[PDB]
Amino acid sequence: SMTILLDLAPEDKEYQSVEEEMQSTIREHRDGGNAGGIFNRYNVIRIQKVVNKKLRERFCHRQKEVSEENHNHHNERMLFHGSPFINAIIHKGFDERHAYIGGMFGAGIYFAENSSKSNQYVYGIGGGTGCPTHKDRSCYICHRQMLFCRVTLGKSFLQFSTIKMAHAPPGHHSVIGRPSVGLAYAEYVIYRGEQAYPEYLITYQIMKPE
Ligand SMILES: Cc1cc(N2CCN(C)[C@@H](C)C2)ncc1-c1ccc(-c2nc3c(CO)cccc3c(=O)[nH]2)cc1
Ligand SMILES: [Zn+2]
Image (cartoon, rainbow, N blue to C red; front, side, top):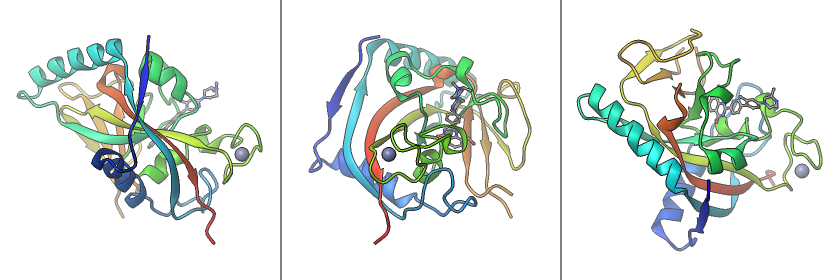
């Protein structure tokens, strides 16, 4: 459906809040930077607010159903999502028919509290072949994009190791993978696309350390 992208000004508190969450949640990955590249900082190019009436309608309708099953609590969290399918997401919304089958919690839609974890999926699973132009997973030239999303978690089912599932457990609305001594970083899983709204579209580069 019809999507409008509104540019946030770098001087605005809103743009600054999104960049602060993005920059401050960067951490070192176990693959030594193979999937997302080697960097300790991003160069934020643009931050846009995604406006889509039909997506907002579907998200708000689902929030009400979740609230009803969760003592009138949405349990909403702002979380990162990196994907080669950014264009489809901002126009058509998140779709569980395009879930990550290979995911450690089964065929769900995966979100991160660490921007660096989502950066590992911008070009595909495991970084795929990298940027389309230079076939480089650590490309410092190409402008990357990721989303900072409103995610309705409702009643979360907490897990610490791999358990493949198709849907959240009975009475639950999401699955959370927690880090332990185990997972390196937390993973947030929804099994219904309408439980996430792609609120912010961030255009950035990973920065090559000096
Ligand atoms: C589902 C899929 C198919 C595909 N394909 C292209 C080639 N082909 C067209 C098909 C084979 C299909 N490429 C990428 C994805 C995909 C996209 C994003 C993620 C993703 N995962 C995350 C995780 C998983 O642990 C944790 C934390 C955060 C994230 C995150 O932000 N994003 C996973 C997979
Ligand atoms: Zn490139």
